[PDB]
Length: 212
Length: 205
Ligand SMILES: Nc1ncnc2c1ncn2[C@@H]1O[C@H](COP(=O)(O)OP(=O)(O)CP(=O)(O)O)[C@@H](O)[C@H]1O
Ligand SMILES: Nc1ncnc2c1ncn2[C@@H]1O[C@H](COP(=O)(O)OP(=O)(O)CP(=O)(O)O)[C@@H](O)[C@H]1O
Ligand SMILES: [Mg+2]
Ligand SMILES: [Mg+2]
Figure 1 (cartoon, protein in one colour):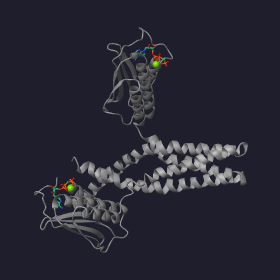
Figure 2 (cartoon, chains in turn red, blue):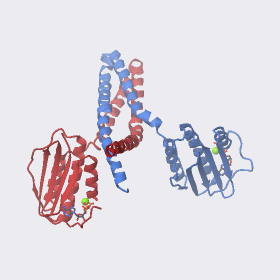
Figure 3 (spheres, rainbow over the protein chains, first blue to last red):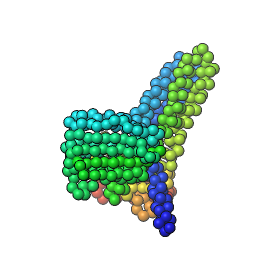
Figure 4 (cartoon, rainbow over the protein chains, first blue to last red):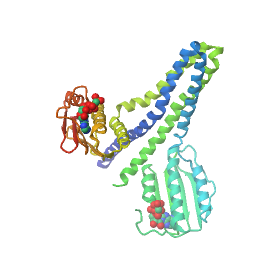
């Protein structure tokens, strides 16, 4: 009714700030890129050209020039190797490993068995999920003081679900949502999924997100 | 707001930043590897077949020039870039001059014409040079504010103004500076009271 009309409106303004902030982003990069890969790539222009001119007039210098070109091609693509490494993102496969290591070295038993694991989930969600995960684990090896920790990750419905439970005690007060907690929620929620918790026996984190 | 705000910020930031890396690799990858290949192949045929070699290098120049342009168009549109470069340029010159550079980004510019940005850059650089030329001051305050419609640099130095009473000789950056701001319908003023003080103004647009 009235509530539907005013949600449509609320979505329109969200999106509007979206496009704007994404733009400002396109930019930080515009400066870095231009600097580096721009001087270099203009130089590639010039040596290309100059090489073509000297092919006959002087095939020696021509060659030497092409040597320098290939050099700068390669290293430039190397710069973007160093660049799409960033925000390329971690895949859970990797985050699970990381955490198995952190839990072992925490003095804690890591309970797992690969259960109905994920396919054709957006790479992005994979990053977020990776994050919340790492944070949850840290919280546990920070306060729970549990000695064992169960975890499963399943493709339920059209929605993916991690669950991370620890036998320790939840050291938090009644409203310590002050911190990777508010962080976690804020996140999943923005991805239109959910985060839930139970301090019944130790601490239990259910993260959910849309997949299929 | 402290965090709902700039947390959802930094998250759409990362949303599209992953998208942006997939586009780098996609576009400039394919392209730049192809540049590798044609470079190489060109070197091989320089003699065996200098014709094909040339043709290959033509296609190379095309691509190298082309890749920069997509990024470049965004850069031309973007504002505040000229001033930032100038600040970096002058901070360096002042440091290396033996001089303290006083600054704090104060109500800095948005949607000023790119042109005015260049002019202002200029007068600025010239002002600085004059200081590190004659003022022999040891510290130098500078601010750049968006005052109402009009933008204003102010560049002050504690040294002494070595100039005579009417040192505004043409072809010197003084007559040059005025000539300029004034042609842009803004203004230039100075005070030799304590050291030297330059107020540049111009229209924001
Ligand atoms: N798995 C767990 N076991 C026991 N206590 C936990 C827990 N997860 C969170 N807590 C408690 O809840 C409170 C809030 O945690 P939150 O995640 O906001 O910050 P933190 O203490 O984990 C450090 P950071 O915010 O840097 O990760 C903490 O005071 C912590 O002791
Ligand atoms: N900030 C400053 N401090 C002290 N003296 C200054 C000054 N700016 C200018 N002057 C004096 O006024 C004169 C005019 O300076 P101006 O910058 O107009 O010409 P210039 O001597 O720098 C050569 P150019 O043509 O390269 O600018 C200078 O010769 C100098 O003696
Ligand atoms: Mg935490
Ligand atoms: Mg001068």
